Image 1 (tube, helix red, strand yellow):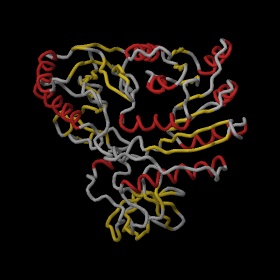
Image 2 (cartoon, rainbow, N blue to C red):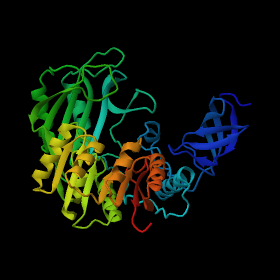
Image 3 (cartoon, rainbow, N blue to C red):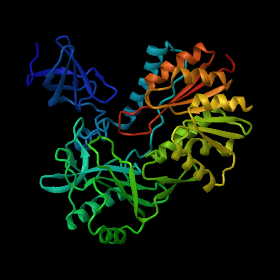
Image 4 (tube, helix red, strand yellow):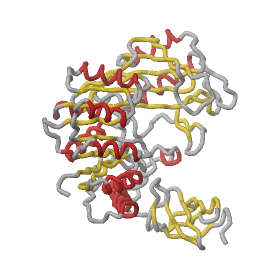
Length: 453
């Protein structure tokens, strides 16, 4: 029976969703960082639980031909790129396999085509938004990212999967915070001023918003700091302050202040302009979010007479992306300011057939149906937990023939598919999309239809 710090020769026989190698020794299932299937390693036992254990590679005996040798290990240990040590073609095959297995094991479905995962051509340097903690590390204010399962900042300048100009702004801000003697936040002490930096840069527009996330309102000589950072980065259009005075894992507090310029940037997606506030949700991989939405559009076979419900519409990106293709878009969104933003974004693009309600999806559907609206397509991008039975039955009660389910969690998608099948919908096609390349994340578009069943 294995002990911690034992060294055992194992063959890696599987890979978890989150990118851990799997070995099976002495009745236990071991999870091993930075170890790929068919690799043979000397494994250092780090921890033994009842049915599972944890290990480390002491030495590679056989390295996989699918290993990417050039990845800095910082990106695995920060969880920035959980699959970054796997060749990109095998990353895609793995995400495809996971979708297929979920549909079979959860929904009992084995006869539906699952397309190979849509990948990114140069799957690096892509995020249009940084959220970096600011902490003192080794006595110096640093920017970086937390080690996995911790709040220990790893100082980083190159974030691998982030816009390099954003990386440069974060470094310039780091150095200005140092020159101006501004103190980083200390979670244990609840001391200091600077908690986080959020930097958004338009993928297409290059417009930059700097958010200083601070514990207190007053930031000494911040006007001179702003004066100098905009000298280095004239593309900065907004310097915002968010005050978070709470002991919480949430990034943002309630109060926002504009210190310079605008309180938003403008960026483009599928040909439309979007005004993006500090706390708005906006896909960080614009290049692949465009392909994701294009996939749902293609699956739904959108016609100019279709009436679309954009369920959980946010600041409007999905419905406004399809608005030019369909008769009417009805968006439901629970957050009123998001509805405000989606109305502004419709107006900015002169889109007049997109209408938003702030309500629950069930109540909006009830009222829309009472108003005579006859939905024909529902586009829904549920949270990780999937849809409720109430939502599924309500969406089915609308009579909508096609439902494009944009999932960030294949497991809850397969569960929801089962109920839609009981309700008379057929699962027609499935397309995984690599929305977050180099990571574990599997995004899936599923087409459900009660036509031709």
